[PDB]
Amino acid sequence: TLGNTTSSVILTNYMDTQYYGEIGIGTPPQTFKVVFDTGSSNVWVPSSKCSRLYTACVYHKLFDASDSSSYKHNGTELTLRYSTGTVSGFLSQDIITVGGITVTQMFGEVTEMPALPFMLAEFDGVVGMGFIEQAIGRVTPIFDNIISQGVLKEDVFSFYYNRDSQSLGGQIVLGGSDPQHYEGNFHYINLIKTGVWQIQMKGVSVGSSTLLCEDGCLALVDTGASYISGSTSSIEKLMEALGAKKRLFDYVVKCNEGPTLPDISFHLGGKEYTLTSADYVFQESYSSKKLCTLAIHAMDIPPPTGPTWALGATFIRKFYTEFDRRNNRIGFALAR
Ligand SMILES: COCCCOc1cc(C(=O)N(C[C@@H]2CNC[C@H]2NS(=O)(=O)c2ccc(C)cc2)C(C)C)ccc1OC
Ligand SMILES: *[C@@H]1O[C@H](CO)[C@@H](O)[C@H](O)[C@H]1NC(C)=O
């Protein structure tokens, strides 16, 4: 069922690495800073039942079911494994408010939240924008519950991630796209299969020559990821081609050599999606005596999804993204 409504959620941009908006859970609503993540399908927030020996829970907003009159008990255990860490807790149901839309949703109340990486998180939880196929415990994703209401103009949602400034951090539009944040026309790539926001990639070039993904590869379009990521192997080759040094969790260049780095192009569908060094280098200075982090890192995503590349905030900043559930495709347009 299609309606005549679009809703939008204003996002906060924290240092070009984290983008999140707010949702309200319960009656009266308890507000949470959440990441709208196309790379996951579950809704979760920290729980009041999280042991205060997990320091992450002392530093985040906790959902208290005892303060919500609309809460429905469930209790089923839930473990969510990310390539960055793990969270576990139990399932609960309540009313969730997302940019005007009110929806009865099943979500995870996280009771185990490791300091790495959640003490570094500015957000409290996640709103999974993925498909039911990848939903842990086969829980209906929030977008599927919003479609069911038959209120949205289109069975799509789109992302705008701005470059850091005190301006608009970003924007998610549910039910459409916002022409104020893109120019030109959308170029669509069909999903390899329904169930994952993953498209075929046919080459990654450093400069003029296609040095990587020559015989094709996968590209997960991940709104919950900060960077463009590849497998340890691909990133090693890419970084050698750029002249970057490996550290513990990132790659660096001498700050003075950042602007001189070659363009990186991603071959997706029809078009070549080019990022210049200004789009992937955290150019904090131009000093020959300082190191500058790159917005590309290695991430070994496990099968069946991985091995795959992931196009995170680094990519979405340059390219406004529309996620089309009706046609199982992803559209890209140059962001304004
Ligand atoms: C862009 O701003 C978003 C905020 C970035 O900051 C952070 C993000 C995180 C983070 O890793 N995630 C989860 C990842 C984002 N998509 C899903 C998952 N990627 S994954 O490769 O494991 C994966 C992909 C696909 C499948 C099927 C399975 C596994 C968030 C959303 C919990 C952690 C700490 C952060 O900061 C301290
Ligand atoms: C929890 O919710 C699921 C639906 O996601 C349901 O099938 C299950 O029976 C519920 N469990 C309890 C104990 O209420």
Image (spheres, rainbow, N blue to C red):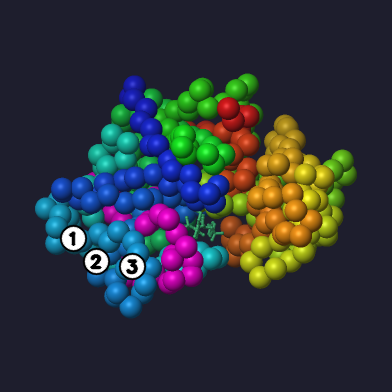
Mark 2 close to ligand 2, CB under 8 Å: no
Residue 110, magenta (yes or no): yes
Kindly identify which residue carries mark 2: 48
Kindly identify which residue carries mark 3: 57
Q: Nearer the viewer, mark 2 or mark 1?
A: 2
Q: Where residue 312 sits in the image (x, y, percent)?
A: 58, 48
Kindly identify which residue carries mark 1: 65
Give, as a single range, the part of the protein colored magenta. 104-132
Total numbered labels placed on residues in the image? 3
Residue 187 as seen in the image, left or right of residue 84:
right
Q: Nearer the viewer, residue 47 or 192?
A: 47
Q: CA distance from mark 3 to mark 2?
A: 8 Å
Q: Residue at x 66, y 70 (%)?
A: 248
Is residue 38 visible in the rendered image? The answer is no
Q: Where residue 92 sits in the image (x, y, percent)?
A: 25, 59
The kind of secondary structure element at disc 3 is helix
Q: Amino acid at mark 1?
A: Ala
Is residue 256 visible in the rendered image? The answer is yes
Q: Earlier in the sequence, mark 2 or mark 1?
A: 2
Please determine whether, in this image, residue 241 is positioned above or below residue 118: above
Q: Amino acid at mark 3?
A: Cys
Q: Nearer the viewer, residue 279 or 301?
A: 279
Q: Nearer the viewer, residue 73 or 195?
A: 73
Q: Say which quarter of the image contains residue 52.
A: bottom left
